[PDB]
Image (cartoon, coloured by chain):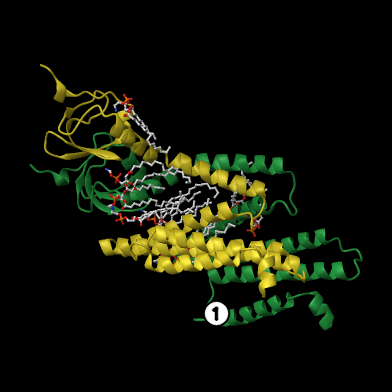
Chain colours: A yellow, B green
């Protein structure tokens, strides 16, 4: 209200004014006016700071002034819920722009819609699992639900992650190189190496055909390199 | 009661009136009068808000006025139980309409009833596991029960989830395309690619027969692409 109320409020509204000035500057985005990824992250961060400052202000108001019946528990529940809502809106907008980019690149409409919906459901589940205390339920129930889900996801996704880990290993310690003829007594991977990727290795066979070998195979089989022979 | 009681109640009945007005508007459902999925979700949410407001009102009444013998612990137990009951009713109605849609599409009636029952039992188990604190019991017992169930479910459902994860991988990084003749030295998948799905890939063999390859195979075998040969 007056100067006395501001003194009783310490310096909180000053933080809100500073955040408003920062948002006005970020409208020009400092060095270059644009948006994307980090812009939404910093906007969400400053919104969280503003909401926390407003919560502190209303808590001080209800403490020093008349208590009335506000029960600040629901006030922190409401501020957390608003933060969750704005985070969900930001994530939905981000995945919508991702779907727009995918459809611009040229892809099946139904497939892109289904993929967007998969990302939607995954985001909702993760946010429910993480935020499930300000409005959530049983600690045991959430722990069990998340444990079952995580066990299933970890068991099911082992092979793709294994391929990518072997790709990292190949990036750091690779027994062959591009253009080397390679072989294996365990599997049929014969040909000359054409490309080394993060998930698969592309090899040109001796009948001029591309062969795509998963990277994890190089972590469990013996690899011979006739391209480096001496005689 | 009178204006003094309303002042002692702060603003809670106003929230109930606002929720009633929102329900009246949702009867016309805003832009288009209809029902389904999100309609039941928002109805359940507003019912939960109304029940929480009523609980706050009765708590304030028993605090400021005569205490009598109400023991607000059973009052919060009752409100949580009512929320659970309305949630169960909504879910049962939703799966009943799902069964109606399935039977309309044309399917064995016994299989539809069995599937509906399965969904009923699964939803009952999940709700008991999640809400098992307001009328629930031992945290150790619930943790153990849910852990055993989740471990069994996660180990049992590994292959289907692996197929769908490999389908997502194929959607993002695919070594072949529609119409490509493909091969493998590890398994018999020879033919031309006709369809790429989320669970299986449909391939036309060279005797004009459809072959359905589970997607997870593409994450562990070497795939040759004679359709991209140069000579
Ligand atoms: C809470 C948990 C969720 C929050 C964390 C996960 C979501 C993060 C989303 C933003 C990722 C960073 C994007 C940065 C950015 O703008 O870069 C673009 C990347 O585009 C892209 O292609 C971006 C694709 C991002 C896909 C993210 C999929 C997440 C699925 C759900 C994960 C759940 C667990 C999260 C911990 C430009 O790049 P470009 O378009 O030019 O690149 C293709 C050419 N090289
Ligand atoms: C206990 C676990 C039980 C298994 C998990 C549930 C799977 C059932 C999902 C079925 C969804 C479904 O059939 O919806 C159709 C497709 O949805 C879809 O696009 C499929 C959605 C896939 C979601 C899978 C769950 C993700 C969970 C992430 C966290 C872990 C509707 O099709 P439409 O209306 O889009 O069709 C438009 C053209 N007619
Ligand atoms: C471990 C986690 C297990 C998770 C199991 C998930 C089961 C999913 C069942 C099917 C859900 C389908 C949802 C769906 O199709 O909704 C679309 C977006 O989802 C939404 O906006 C609603 C998302 C609902 C997520 C529920 C997750 C509960 C986890 C606890 C609507 O999209 P549209 O506009 O095309 O729809 C109109 C045309 N059908
Ligand atoms: C968990 C989530 C994902 C984790 C992401 C991990 C990121 C990278 C971590 C590993 C960094 C390795 C740095 C190696 C440095 C280096 O030069 O090492 C050389 C390769 O060694 C080697 O043999 C390096 C092998 C690295 C294998 C990494 C396996 C995948 C991890 C997942 C030989 O060492 P030197 O001292 O003789 O160097 C002299 C010649 N460069
Ligand atoms: C969270 C909740 C619980 C989750 C449980 C795990 C679920 C597992 C499901 C599978 C996860 C697979 C992650 C794949 C990484 C995506 C890589 C990506 O998009 O970028 C590629 C580059 O790879 C790279 O840059 C290499 C990335 C190395 C692997 C990532 C290491 C950390 C693991 C992340 C998940 C951990 C959980 C593009 O290039 P490309 O591969 O197409 O190009 C060469 C192909 N020939
Ligand atoms: C508490 C945990 C349970 C609450 C979350 C899980 C239940 C969610 C039920 C609603 C899902 C979203 C439905 C949205 C909707 O109306 O879309 C219709 C989807 O129809 C459909 O076909 C809907 C099928 C939904 C199947 C859901 C099976 C759930 C089994 C139990 C899961 C337990 C774990 C949950 C975390 C229209 O689509 P349409 O009919 O035109 O589509 C076929 C043509 N493309
Ligand atoms: C400890 C674990 C022990 C194993 C798990 C329980 C297995 C026993 C279930 C048998 C059910 C059964 O035979 O009931 C008949 C079939 O029910 C059915 O329609 C099958 C019900 C299947 C339920 C399986 C358990 C689901 C649990 C979900 C959470 C995890 C009822 O026949 P009707 O009256 O429908 O026949 C109408 C035509 N005469
Ligand atoms: C991990 C979790 C393990 C769970 C094990 C579940 C064992 C289930 C045993 C068989 C239950 C059959 C239930 C049944 O047939 O009830 C139908 C609907 O179920 C109902 O409405 C009642 C479902 C009761 C589920 C109890 C789960 C307890 C979990 C703790 C009745 O349907 P109808 O009208 O056709 O029946 C009359 C004609 N049989
Ligand atoms: C847990 C429950 C279910 C989780 C659902 C996961 C949702 C999607 C998460 C992965 C998003 C990947 C986005 C990739 C974007 C992209 O363009 O990446 C390209 C493919 O990379 C790649 O190689 C992408 C491989 C993605 C493997 C996902 C495995 C299944 C996860 C489950 C190469 O990237 P670039 O920079 O060359 O882009 C330029 C060319 N697009
Ligand atoms: C919860 C309690 C604990 C549960 C533990 C896990 C239990 C595992 C049991 C198996 C679960 C399998 C989920 C299947 C997903 C249903 C997909 C669905 O209905 O939509 C399809 C589209 O798929 C898609 O849209 C792709 C979906 C990608 C997989 C979903 C990623 C998250 C994992 C969800 C469960 C996690 C827990 C329809 O299309 P279609 O497949 O018929 O068409 C191409 C076929 N050729």
Q: In screen coordinates, is A202 left or right of A33?
A: left
- B149 in relation to B9, above or below: above
Q: Nearer the viewer, residue B111 or B63?
A: B63
Quarter holding residue A69: bottom right
Q: Residue at x 61, y 63 (%)?
A: A11
Q: Residue at x 61, y 49 (%)?
A: A142
Host chain of mark 1: B
- B166 in relation to B75, above or below: above
- A20 in relation to A148, above or below: below
- The x and y percentages for residue A170 are 29, 32
Q: Nearer the viewer, residue B91 or B141?
A: B141
- The x and y percentages for residue B181 are 19, 46
Q: Which residue is mark 1?
A: B29
Which quadrant does the C terminus of chain A fall into? top left
- The x and y percentages for residue B136 are 74, 50
Q: Nearer the viewer, residue A112 or B207?
A: A112
């Amino acid at each position: 209200e007056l100067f006395t109320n501001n003194a009783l409020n310490l310096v909180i509204i000053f933080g809100s004014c500073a955040a408003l000035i920062l948002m006005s500057f970020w409208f020009r985005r400092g060095n270059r006016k644009r948006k994307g990824f980090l812009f939404h992250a910093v906007q969400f961060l400053i919104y969280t700071i503003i909401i926390s400052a407003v919560g502190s202000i209303i808590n001080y108001v209800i403490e020093n002034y008349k208590l009335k019946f506000i029960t600040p528990g629901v006030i922190d529940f409401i501020c957390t819920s608003l933060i969750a809502v704005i985070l969900t809106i930001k994530l939905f907008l981000l995945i919508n722009q991702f779907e727009k980019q995918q459809i611009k690149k040229g892809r099946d409409i139904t497939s892109a819609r289904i993929m967007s919906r998969i990302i939607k459901i995954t985001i909702i589940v993760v946010l429910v699992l993480l935020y499930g205390e300000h409005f959530g339920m049983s600690l045991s129930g959430l722990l069990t639900f998340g444990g079952i889900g995580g066990l299933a996801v970890g068991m099911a996704g082992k092979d793709i992650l294994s391929n990518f880990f072997s790709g990292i290993m190949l990036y750091f310690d690779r027994p062959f190189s591009i253009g080397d003829w390679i072989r294996s007594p365990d599997r049929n991977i014969e040909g000359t190496v054409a490309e080394i990727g993060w998930r698969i290795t592309k090899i040109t066979t001796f009948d001029n055909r591309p062969l795509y070998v998963p990277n994890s195979l190089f972590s469990s089989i013996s690899v011979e390199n006739p391209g480096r022979m001496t005689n």
